[PDB]
Image: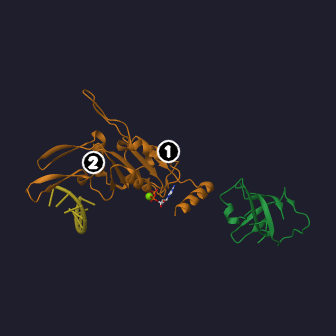
Chain colours: A green, B orange, C yellow
Amino acid sequence: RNENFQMSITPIKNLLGRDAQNFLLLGLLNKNFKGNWSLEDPSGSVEIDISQTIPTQGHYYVPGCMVLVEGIYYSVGNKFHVTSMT
Amino acid sequence: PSIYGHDHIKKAILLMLMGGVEKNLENGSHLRGDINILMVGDPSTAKSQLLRFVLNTASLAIATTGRGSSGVGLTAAVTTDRETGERRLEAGAMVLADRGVVCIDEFDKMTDVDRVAIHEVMEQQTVTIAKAGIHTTLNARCSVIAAANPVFGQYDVNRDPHQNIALPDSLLSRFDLLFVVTDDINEIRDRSISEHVLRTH
DNA sequence: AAAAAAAAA
Ligand SMILES: Nc1ncnc2c1ncn2[C@@H]1O[C@H](COP(=O)(O)OP(=O)(O)OP(=O)(O)O)[C@@H](O)[C@H]1O
Ligand SMILES: [Mg+2]
């Protein structure tokens, strides 16, 4: 319902067949059973790359909070290289 | 346009539908003029659909199944006319396709005996009937396209090509082009083909 | 004359 959003988000499960392309997605932020950072969606779940993430200041980024994730998928492994989070 | 990939197969079909000219010589007898193409591959790789498309788009073609045919009845038959009371030859499946193209499915499942009936046609493009007092040579200058499955359920790329194909080399040497197709699993191709097939439906 | 089922090799 936001005024700005009328770019469109993409479900997690639709990230399997594409790579080297930017995407926007949101979901629950938490830790997997292995111990890495993952995002959850009703469609599915992916992993998170944090090494080059610039977050929007003014928020308490805590596990269990919905976050808008922008980054580039990589099908070489399963790492979603996030470039910003808000 | 509804078949994804197989571009070289499409080019081969295009060149086969309008193949080269036949040659005749006062001393060299006769030279074959057209092209025959055989394809082998693991199941569910869109061979029969391409065969049906070639049937639909050709000027003249006849559909034939390996299991549902008999070689002796494929070329000619002996039938007694009810009016004249005499027996006359009835044209077989391949004779009707003179100057046309014949498509055969389940070729590797087709009986070995009748295979020789095909080889004769591949030899001089003429069938000879000598039975019940009729001695005639019938012209059949058609091209044949066939698709067959390997001996195993799926193609083994690590094995001898002769090992994977049940047909003897004697007739395999006749075909000008041999094509082997495999459905290699790749997520990019899987997504592309899934999008295409969903678009078609 | 040509297709289809049965028992023995
Ligand atoms: N590249 C493709 N584009 C579109 N449809 C395809 C493609 N590959 C396979 N198919 C689909 O696969 C299905 C299998 O078709 P078909 O039986 O004719 O294939 P085949 O490779 O000839 O298989 P078989 O060995 O069983 O005869 C079809 O419904 C066809 O639409
Ligand atoms: Mg098929």
Q: Answer with the quarter of the image where residue A34 lies.
A: bottom right
| Helix, strand or loop for disc 2 | helix
Q: Identify the residue at image location x=59%, y=54%.
A: B189
Residue at mark 2 to residue at mark 1: CA–CA distance: 30 Å
**Amino acid type of disc 2?**
Ala
Disc number for residue B117: 2
**Residue B157 location (% of width, % of height):** 52, 48
Q: Identify the residue at image location x=72%, y=56%.
A: A77
Please indicate, yes or no, whether residue A25 appears anywhere in the rendered image: yes
| Badge 2: chain ID | B
**Residue B75 location (% of width, % of height):** 24, 50
Ligand 1 within 8 angstroms of badge 2 C-beta: no
Q: Identify the residue at image location x=35%, y=47%.
A: B144
Disc number for residue B33: none
Are the residues flagged by discs 2 and 1 in contact, CB closer than 8 Å?
Answer: no
Q: Which residue is mark 1?
A: B8
**Amino acid type of disc 1?**
His
| Badge 1: chain ID | B
**Near-viewer residue (B68 or A17):** A17
Q: Is residue B126 left or right of residue A63?
A: left
Mark 1 crowd level (few <14, some 14–19, many ≥20, 10 Å Cα): few
